[PDB]
Amino acid sequence: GVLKGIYLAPYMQVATALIGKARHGNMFRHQVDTMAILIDYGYIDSVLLKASLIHDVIENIEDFNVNEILSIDSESGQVYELVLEVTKKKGQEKTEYLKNIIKNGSEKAKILKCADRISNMISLGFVTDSEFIERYCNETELYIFPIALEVNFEMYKELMALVVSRRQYLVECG
Amino acid sequence: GVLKGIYLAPYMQVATALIGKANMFRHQVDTMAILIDYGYIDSVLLKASLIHDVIENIEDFNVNEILSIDSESGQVYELVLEVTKKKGQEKTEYLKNIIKNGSEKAKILKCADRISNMISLGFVTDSEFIERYCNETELYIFPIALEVNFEMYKELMALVVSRRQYLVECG
Ligand SMILES: [Cl-]
Ligand SMILES: [Mn+2]
Ligand SMILES: [Mn+2]
Image 1 (cartoon, each protein chain N blue to C red):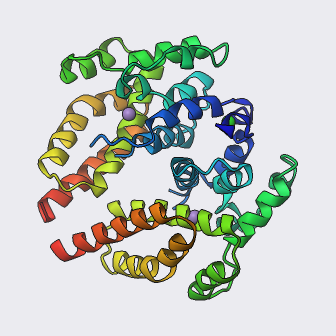
Image 2 (image 1 turned 60 degrees about the horizontal axis):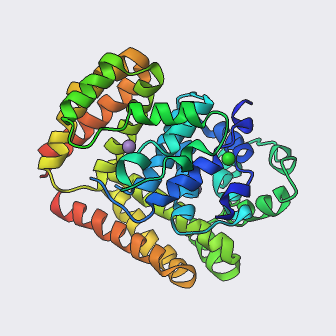
C-alpha cells in the first residue's frame, strides 16, 4: 500500500501542457499510459512514476520552464535528473541516444524507456503509414529489446509480442 | 487546474486489484486520462473513472475498500454503479438504460470508457468482433456522446471509421 502515499497529481498537472499534440499518438494520454504500464509491472517508485508522467514534457514543449518540475516537492530534483536521462538533446543522432541509454543510463531510465516504448508500440495499432511501422518495429527490436532483457524479462515479452503483431499486420495488409 | 487538490492515488490503489486480467488495469488509468484530456477536472468523475470496472470485473469485491477512502467515496460508488451492468442483464438494455436514466457524469464516463475500449480494438484481429463492437458503438454510444460532448463524438466516429476501414482493406 505504498502507492496510496505518492503525490502524483502535480506531475499530471504539468503533463496537461501536452494536451493538443501528436507524435507518430496523443502525447498527454501517452504520459499517463506510461505511468499505468510501470504500475502494471509493479514499479511503485516515487521518482520513476513521477518522471513517467512528464518524461516527454521537456522534449516536446518549446521553452518549457523547468521550474514547473523543480518547485513541486523534495524529490523534484531526482525526477528532473531522470527525465533528462530519457530526453534526446536537440539534433542528437536518435541511434546514439538509444545506444547511450543502454551504455550509461540508470536502472530507472532503462525501465522508463521500456514502458515508454511499450506505450508507443501500442499506439502503432491505429497508424497506416506502413514504412513508419516497419522502421519503428526495427528500431524497437535493435535498440529497446536489449534494454528490456537487462531490466525486465516480462517487458521484453510484451515488446516482442507487439513487434511480431505489427509486423504480422504489414505482411497481411500494408 | 483544480487537479492538484484531487486525492486520486487511493483510487489508483484500488484499481491495482485488476492487475492480472483481460488489459483492465491500463484501461482504468487510460479512461481517467481521456477525461482529463477532454478537460473534465471533476473529483467524483475522475475518482470513479479509476475504478469504474472494479465492481463489474471482481466477483466478491469488498465495496468498503471504496466507501472508506474519503467524503466523496459514496458519490463515487453511486457513479460506478450507474455504469456497472447487473450480473444477468441484456447489454442492449443496459446501454439503452444509461442514455435514458444515467446522470450527465455516467454518460461522460461511458463515452470515455468506450473511447478507451475502441482504441484497444487496434491490436485485435477477430474481425467479426471488431464489426459487432463498431456497430454497438455507432448505435448506442454515438448518441450518448452527442448529448454530453461533441468532441468525444468526433473521436468515437474517427475510431469506428478507422476500424471499419481496416475490415474493408483486409478480411
Ligand atoms: Cl495523485
Ligand atoms: Mn514517450
Ligand atoms: Mn470499462
